Image: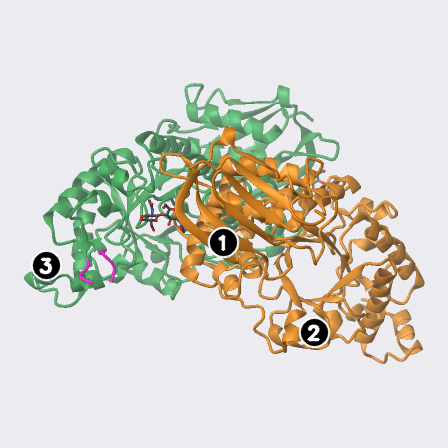
Chain colours: A orange, B green
Amino acid sequence: ALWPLPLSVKMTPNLLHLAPENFYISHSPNSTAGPSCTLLEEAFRRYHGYIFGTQVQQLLVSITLQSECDAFPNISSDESYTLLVKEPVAVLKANRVWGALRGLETFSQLVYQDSYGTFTINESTIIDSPRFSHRGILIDTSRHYLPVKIILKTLDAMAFNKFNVLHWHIVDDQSFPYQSITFPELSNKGSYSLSHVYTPNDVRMVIEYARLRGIRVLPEFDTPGHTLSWGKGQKDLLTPCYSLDSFGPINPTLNTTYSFLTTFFKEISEVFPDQFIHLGGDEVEFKCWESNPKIQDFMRQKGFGTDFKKLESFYIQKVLDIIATINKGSIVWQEVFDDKAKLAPGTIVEVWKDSAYPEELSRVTASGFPVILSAPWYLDLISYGQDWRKYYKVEPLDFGGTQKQKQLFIGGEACLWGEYVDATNLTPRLWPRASAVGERLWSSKDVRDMDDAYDRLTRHRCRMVERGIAAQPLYAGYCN
Amino acid sequence: ALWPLPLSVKMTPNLLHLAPENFYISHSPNSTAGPSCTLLEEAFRRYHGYIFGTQVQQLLVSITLQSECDAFPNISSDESYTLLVKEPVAVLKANRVWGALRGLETFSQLVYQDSYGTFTINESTIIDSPRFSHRGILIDTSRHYLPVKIILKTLDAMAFNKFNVLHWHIVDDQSFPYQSITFPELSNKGSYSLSHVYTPNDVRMVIEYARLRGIRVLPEFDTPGHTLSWGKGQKDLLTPCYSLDSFGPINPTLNTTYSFLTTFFKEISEVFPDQFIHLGGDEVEFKCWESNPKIQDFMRQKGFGTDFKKLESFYIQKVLDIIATINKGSIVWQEVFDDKAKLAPGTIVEVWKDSAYPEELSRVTASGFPVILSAPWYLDLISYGQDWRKYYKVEPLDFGGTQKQKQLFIGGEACLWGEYVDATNLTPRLWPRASAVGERLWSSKDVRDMDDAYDRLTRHRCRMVERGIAAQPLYAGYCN
Ligand SMILES: *[C@@H]1O[C@H](CO)[C@@H](O[C@@H]2O[C@H](CO)[C@@H](O)[C@H](O)[C@H]2NC(C)=O)[C@H](O)[C@H]1NC(C)=O
Ligand SMILES: *[C@@H]1O[C@H](CO)[C@@H](O[C@@H]2O[C@H](CO)[C@@H](O)[C@H](O)[C@H]2NC(C)=O)[C@H](O)[C@H]1NC(C)=O
């Protein structure tokens, strides 16, 4: 009942038993980590509870290289590990902390109770490492505010599924819950109310909680579209519409815009330790820009004609430059690439449009850019039945391209947009549907037996329920 | 923020205030009900909590006719009431208890807190009575066992939406959680486990809890199909398949079948006080019957040829006769009617097939039978977006027929089949999507303004959340 299925699993018929008040998880004497390592100490204690909640007396954990205990995970973090389950001492070995965390999760999935309640595990050897290194979940806290607690629960569920990126789509048109220190009015005027805000301390908590599970927090502050809530607190930022709404996208012709974005993104570069900031750039509407006289003036000032993609490109290029100047990487939705903006090498493009997405993957990778797939994994788009199967069956590298292009595919994200989701329904909708995406991104390409996937996923789902994650059923049945 | 919208609402701009520890709900001195009426006393206390959780000091409740306090509700129960909100004493008047319960719900939807927290209500007069008298929710506890607590919560939510029938699809192929006293082996061998069973006392609790909210409990013990779990404990009941599964539908050629069903339904007639028992009769597969030699013998014994609809009809007619002999009414899925079984007058046909359902309504009503619609309200069939709108827009009497035929349309049910539903996801999936069906069945035919429906339903949904029902959002937004 392993989920995701490890790279290599070799088991024996030899059963070993565990005694809850006589079973410890500890540092091997040769490890680079010790009691000082908060990350490993907290993991040891919480996995003790998950496991229990002929005798293997100890699970020794050996970190081989500089542990990276006090650091934040990044895209190249080594998550590989081996697990040797034997008597009297099992051994978890990993290059870094990140692999040990993954291995602790797998160890807990190997321990089970027999018919008489006896804690049991098979003698075994597991070798494991992920297929892709970007394995994300997108949450949307603008369409509905999500309390900190449900973000923490999602992070727990992500750890159980070996996801490593929380893509936090923190703000959007409807509300601005991010409390900015340098610009207090963004949240004061843009949030749904004062109890629908994320304080600097709420943000630190999510980041720390994520780090302890080897999860990166990738902030998205989408512009120039999806910014209506930004205009409540930052005057003169948004374009006024001469007529179909009242305000449109960010005004890209004003110097106050870029001065605001410089100061703002500098704050973001300090608050969020991850190397990458998602700049968005999706679904920019041009009707407002088209109907605005000052923008029309600006359009002819540098020969953009009637092609508003060039104005969008001009805006996005200035924002990409601001991110580069503060020494961070940028991630962008495909539109930015499709509308012919000039991107610096290293800029990650996220492919989300469901029409001809394999051909989009080819174009992006052929142009040299690293790529992330979300298109077929829009979990907000619910449907009747076992839709986990369609997410599972996706083979992400079935697009046209050389091996060099396929090496630019770094991973994917399962997206849960928030128009119809809040705390009342987020968890059942997210899990175990995202578990299908988690295996596809962790496990080998050839792991696709549907009967076996169903067998392991129902049991994994029951395990998520036992641990406090209200994951919905796959089909008729029961747990325990 | 009324939901469902009452028949007639007339309000004044005059505001009156309420004092929580100086506001009582009591029996008018001329009422037929008094302190002895448990049903009204418990409602008074729980609505006090819902309301609060120039001065109107009292809400007096007057029952005009024999109250029916100690009785179970039935199809012809009078749920009409008037509500006069004035100072110092408001008055709720109803023919029976059933109308007073509806009126208490409406009264609580009229009380609100202003910006400074002051409990306020407008002076007003409301006259109300339902458009249809059968207003049901179908729950399925076979595909997944639902704990008693979530059935009780659903009943609370139903009361808030003025639904009056719990259609309890208690058993099916996958499990038999109904503990039968006369046949203990049905649950002992057919349930998912011994903790996935409904004891006689669990059943009484649900019935009583329902009664206190004016809700009828309609049991469904579906036969001859949907009976695989029945065969674990009752040997020789199901037809053995000569080959695609192992067992098929109930064997209709054996006398032990009918002797079993007589004893069984007699137990059901005593356990469930409602006048009606749903016999099911949907999706009977003939391949097993066709492949069975003894059934082939039986088929020629009374000239049924190769038409297995006649054997199904023969079976169903014997079951309808058993129900008639114990003095109960029968409800049946449309297939029983479509396959030309002879139904006694009064037999209710439930139309569930989504293809040409208006024409099905015509055929059933033209033949003289009372009809219930579920076809367009299959809430298990989820989809992206505001699907509450499609359920709301259904106008049930848009079928071909005379006024006499339209008088045979007694109501409808919103169905939540259980293949993909259990305690982790039932509530968010059910509410407020079923609220759309509740208004369509309670309110006037001409109540269909979508903007107004959206305005009242978001607020109603926030009210359900405040009262402990985790109803999912309609669209982006927030509560409070
Ligand atoms: C883990 O060990 C158990 C116990 O030996 C294995 O289970 C049995 O396998 C043996 C030999 O294949 C069979 O004779 C038994 O019928 C199996 N069950 C029982 C009750 O002992 C199990 O296969 C092992 N796990 C793996 C994948 O190797
Ligand atoms: C309930 O009473 C309130 C208060 O009088 C009504 O609200 C106001 O209506 C008056 C006159 O139409 C307006 O001058 C106010 O602007 C309204 N609000 C306030 C703050 O007083 C409300 O309309 C009444 N409800 C109904 C449907 O009759």
Per the rendering, the mark at residue A364 is 2
Split into 4 quadrants, where in the image is the C terminus of chain B?
top right
Is any atom of residue A275 visible in this view? Answer: yes
Q: Is residue A102 left or right of residue B298?
A: right
Gap in angstroms between the C-alphas marked 3 and 1: 53 Å
Name the residue rendered at 81%, 72% in the picture.
Answer: A313
Q: Which residue is denoted by mark 1 in the rendering?
A: B445
Disc 3 or disc 1, which is closer to the eye?
3
Q: Is residue B452 left or right of residue B135?
A: right
Crowd band around label 2 with a 10 angstrom C-alpha radius: few (<14), some (14–19), many (20+):
many
- Mark 3 and ligand 1: say if the CB distance to the nearest ligand atom is below 8 Å: no
| Marks 3 and 2 share the same chain | no
Chain of the residue that carries numbered disc 2 in the rendered image: A
Chain of the residue that carries numbered disc 3 in the rendered image: B
Gap in angstroms between the C-alphas marked 3 and 2: 67 Å
Q: Is residue A359 magenta?
A: no
**Nearer-the-camera pick, A359 or A383:** A359
First to last magenta residue range: B241-247
In the depicted structure, whether residue A426 falls above or below residue A358: above
Name the residue rendered at 25%, 57% in the picture.
Answer: B336
- SS assignment at label 2: helix
In the depicted structure, whether residue B396 falls above or below residue B231: below
Q: Amino acid at mark 2?
A: Val
Q: Amino acid at mark 1?
A: Lys
- Residue B207 image point, x, y percent: 36, 33
Q: Quadrant of ligand 2?
A: top right
Secondary structure character of the magenta stretch overall: loop
Is any atom of residue B464 visible in this view? Answer: no
Q: Which residue is denoted by mark 3 in the rendering?
A: B294
Name the residue rendered at 55%, 44% in the picture.
Answer: A91
- Residue B232 image point, x, y percent: 23, 45
